[PDB]
Structures are given as structure tokens and as C-alpha cells.
Length: 207
Length: 206
Ligand SMILES: *[C@@H]1O[C@H](CO[C@H]2O[C@@H](C)[C@@H](O)[C@@H](O)[C@@H]2O)[C@@H](O[C@@H]2O[C@H](CO)[C@@H](O[C@@H]3O[C@H](CO[C@H]4O[C@H](CO)[C@@H](O)[C@H](O[C@@H]5O[C@H](CO)[C@@H](O[C@@H]6O[C@H](CO)[C@H](O)[C@H](O)[C@H]6O)[C@H](O)[C@H]5NC(C)=O)[C@@H]4O)[C@@H](O)[C@H](O[C@H]4O[C@H](CO)[C@@H](O)[C@H](O)[C@@H]4O[C@@H]4O[C@H](CO)[C@@H](O)[C@H](O)[C@H]4NC(C)=O)[C@@H]3O)[C@H](O)[C@H]2NC(C)=O)[C@H](O)[C@H]1NC(C)=O
Ligand SMILES: *[C@@H]1O[C@H](CO[C@@H]2O[C@@H](C)[C@@H](O)[C@@H](O)[C@@H]2O)[C@@H](O[C@@H]2O[C@H](CO)[C@@H](O[C@@H]3O[C@H](CO[C@H]4O[C@H](CO)[C@@H](O)[C@H](O)[C@@H]4O[C@@H]4O[C@H](CO)[C@@H](O)[C@H](O)[C@H]4NC(C)=O)[C@@H](O)[C@H](O[C@H]4O[C@H](CO)[C@@H](O)[C@H](O)[C@@H]4O)[C@@H]3O)[C@H](O)[C@H]2NC(C)=O)[C@H](O)[C@H]1NC(C)=O
Image (cartoon, rainbow over all chains, first blue to last red; front, side, top):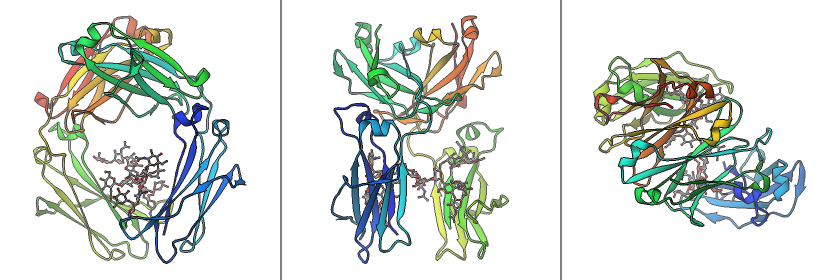
């Protein structure tokens, strides 16, 4: 019957005390004969009652959709306390228990490196700026680009890729006009991760 | 049961010596009704090229019947549509799956190689970067080489949609720092249909 999907807090939310991380328990495919949905939240097996469940909203294919949000602490997620969403519906045989938490392993300090555009690409109107981050663990990390103190708009970040040593890596490309690079403009790659001290480090890139 | 249809690998379609093939995977087959039949259609015209691989009983007490359809190199590159028709007693109606190559004019990939970061030269192993962008569709294969021998210590990111509509990716080759500083020449091999003869390569060295 109903399908339960659990979404972890975003990487930036847990790493910054200003932001508020949340775990989302989305349930879809809810029929009208059994529309009521009940959520049970557990933290390391201990039930909590500080969640906020919103009323069911009917979708466009004759089914409802219910979302339950549990607020988590910054250190609790960084300590990896598992969060279990137990969804109970009268059409289900047994309540569905979905569990998610931080990736099991040892936090390794990320290594951020920046690469200038290739000399062959200098003949084009568009050049590529490369930010290489390697050796970080777990895979939840934030990569951003800014210049002159303001963020850049047209940049892309590749998904993390697991290496052979048990750590992840990814690439970030910022494409700017060749005139901007030749004028010695400073482009920086901001990286936020759990292993980083204060969860922040930065490297500058320029001609 | 469920029907999964998969396209051929990019390298197979670009080399005549290779054998591109379309794979139709059927899962969720019950033991009571294990009879599975395959019908293949190429642009409406039926082809009888169904050769069923040996089945596989999984860890949930079901089967995984896989059918392989080898297609011509030029036929796939022309945008022809291939249909996999699967019939089973547990299915109320036969399931038809049709897949084809992404439509649109091919764009020539632009191959660029990046030397390892100067700050990264403090590690025992460095990483070589090969940037391939501006190609279409996303089907592409990247391989490494050095003095005529493949370099099998690399990872490659999946193609990523770009702002202009093309695709880009990065290939990271991890080698010994000593080898890079000795002047060795490493080649980044790219196989895309838009390229003439479906092949090009850019060499990277110190
Ligand atoms: C009982 O079990 C069976 C099988 O038993 C095993 O199940 C697995 C999961 C194990 O856990 C194990 O316990 C059991 O032994 C069950 O069937 C399984 O069901 C899984 C879902 O629960 C399913 O998961 C899929 O994962 C895909 C991720 O891709 C990666 O994983 C598999 C391999 O693990 C491969 O797809 C990829 O590897 C491929 O594998 C091939 C091996 O050679 C190669 O492909 C072809 O090889 C040829 C060889 O010559 C040619 O080269 C050809 O060109 C190749 O294409 C290839 O080499 C290799 N590649 C690599 C890199 O290794 C890959 O590793 C995922 O993509 C699947 O697709 C789904 O995913 C979503 C799931 O939420 C779904 O929502 C999506 O919609 C998506 O479907 C499609 O998405 C498209 C996106 O746009 C849509 O366009 C499309 O329309 C849509 N499809 C439809 C119909 O709408 C999927 O998640 C497992 O793959 C499957 N098991 C196996 C072995 O395949 C079964 O459920 C159970 N039965 C019951 C119960 O009855
Ligand atoms: C009836 O309609 C239902 C609702 O669909 C709506 O109506 C239709 C007509 C269209 O208009 C839709 O656009 C519309 O949404 C259907 O429910 C859907 O079922 C599918 C099952 O195949 C669900 O797919 C799942 O998607 C996960 C991604 O999560 C995003 O999915 C939606 C993408 O469209 C999006 O709407 C969701 O909001 C969700 O967005 C995320 O929200 C979290 C909230 O915290 C954010 O943090 C994220 O950043 C958001 N991400 C994005 C991309 O927006 C998939 O990930 C998942 O696959 C994999 O999930 C995990 C990993 O995440 C794996 O472990 C797992 O094994 C699996 O491989 C899954 O496929 C889809 O989400 C459902 N729709 C909604 C709104 O929930 C019904 O299927 C349909 N029924 C029928 C009979 O037609």
C-alpha cells in the first residue's frame, strides 16, 4: 500500500548551529478507505514526541500524501544517532520502519585543491575553473563558489565519487568569461564538512 | 513481474570490432509461473534475435531472466527504436518497453587535461584531471593510457547536464607522484560519435 521515504538533513543544516537540521518522513500512495496515517519517531530506540505532522493532502492520482518532520540536534546527527520513522496505516500488514543516520565510518579531513583552466581551453570564450576535494568522509559535504565576496551563478558540482581507500572525492566547475580570468579575478571554492575545523575552509584561484 | 530495458555501452557502438547489444531484464518471476517469452521490435518490424541468457534465482526466491538483443552500430546511431515485449502468466497483459538513443544533433566533445594542483604535490600520489565537455548525447567513454599501456587507477564522474544543454564530466587518474615528475606522458582517450573516427586523445605531462 503506502510507500515510506525518509530524507536525511541537508549537509549544511547539521554543520551550522544557525541552521536547523530536520529529518523528513514522506508517505505517499494513501487510499481513501484507509487515509489516516500515524508516525512514530525513535532516536537510538527511544521514542520522541517533538515532531510536527501536517494534515494529509490529496494528490492528483486519487491518493493522499502525508509528511512528518522531526527536528534533530546538530551534535546528535554528527554523533550519528539513528532516526526511525514508524508509519502505521490500517491498509498495511505491519507498520513500516525506515531508519536513516550519518554514514558509518571515520570522519576524515577533506583536502581542497583548485586547478587553473587548461591552456588548450584558453582559445575559447568560456574557460573552466576546477575545485578538487578529496579524502573526505562521509559523503555529506557542501561546495560553493564566490568571487569578490559575492557568490557566482553559473557553476556546477559533480556528485561525490568513492575512491579505493574508503574516501570520497568530487569536482566543481565554475565557467567564467576569458576576460574575467585574464584580469586576475579571484575565485574561491568554499567547502563545509564535519571533519573541517569550524566546518569551513577556503582556497583562492586566480590567473 | 517487471521489465527493465538497457541501452548498449558507448564504446561498443563506436567500434565495428565490438558488439553493441540491448539488454532486456525481467525480474519478479514467480516459481509457479516461470514461463517468459520475449518479442523484439525494431521500428515496428519484428526481429527474432532473442537469445535468453540463463536465469538466476535471487535472494528473495524469484528469477531474473535476461534477454540480449545485439543491434547494428549504425542502426543504433540513427535513432531507431527498439521494443522489448515480455509475456508471463503472472502479468495481466504483456509489458512492452521501448528505448532509443537521445534525439538531437551530436556535439563535438572538447578534451582538456589539467595538471595536478601545486598544493597537491605534497602527497605521495597525485591526481590527473581530464575535462570533456560540450558533447551530446551523454553516451561517452573515457580511458587512460601511458606509453601504449592502459592506466587502470582512475575514476570518472557520470555525465552532468550543463547550462547550454550539453554534458560534461571529469576523469581523475591517480598515479605515483614520482612518475608525474619524471616526465612521463599520459593520454586521455575519449570515444564520442561526433568526433571524426569516433576517437580523439589529449596528452598530459609535466
Ligand atoms: C528479487 O530480487 C531481484 C534481484 O535480486 C537482487 O536484487 C538486488 C537489488 C540485490 O539487493 C540482491 O539482494 C538480489 O540478489 C530484484 O530485482 C532488483 O531490484 C532492484 C530494486 O529493488 C533493482 O535496483 C535497480 O538499481 C539500478 C541501479 O543501477 C545499478 O545497479 C544494477 C546492478 O546492481 C544495474 O542497473 C547497474 O549495473 C549494470 O548492470 C549490468 C550488468 O552487466 C550492465 O547493464 C548492461 O550490461 C550489458 C552487458 O553487456 C551491456 O553493457 C548494457 O549496455 C548494459 O546496460 C552494466 O554493465 C552495469 N553497470 C555498472 C556500472 O555496473 C548499476 O550498477 C537502478 O538504475 C534501477 O532503476 C530504477 O531505479 C529506481 C528505484 O527507486 C526507479 O524508481 C527508477 O524509475 C529506475 O527505473 C527506470 O529509471 C529510468 C530513469 O529515467 C526511467 O527512464 C525508466 O522508465 C525506469 N524504469 C521503469 C520500468 O519505469 C533499479 O533501482 C535491481 O537492479 C534488481 N536486481 C538486479 C540484479 O538487477 C527484485 O525486485 C526481487 N523480485 C521480487 C521481489 O519479486
Ligand atoms: C501518484 O502521485 C504521487 C506523487 O507524484 C506527484 O504527482 C505526479 C502526477 C507528478 O506530478 C509528480 O511530479 C508529483 O510529485 C507518486 O508518488 C511518487 O512516487 C515515487 C516512487 O517512484 C517517488 O519517487 C521517489 O523520489 C525520491 C526523490 O525524492 C523526491 O521525489 C520527488 C521527485 O519528483 C519530489 O516530489 C519529492 O518531494 C522528493 O523531493 C525531495 O524532498 C526532500 C525533502 O526533505 C528534499 O530534501 C530533497 O532535496 C528533494 N529532492 C528532490 C529531487 O526534489 C527518490 O530518491 C526515490 O528513489 C530512491 O530514493 C532513496 C534515495 O533518496 C533510495 O534509498 C531508494 O531506494 C530509491 O532508490 C523515489 O523514487 C516520488 O517521490 C513520489 N512523489 C512524491 C511527491 O512523493 C505516486 O507514485 C503516484 N502513483 C500513481 C499510481 O501514479
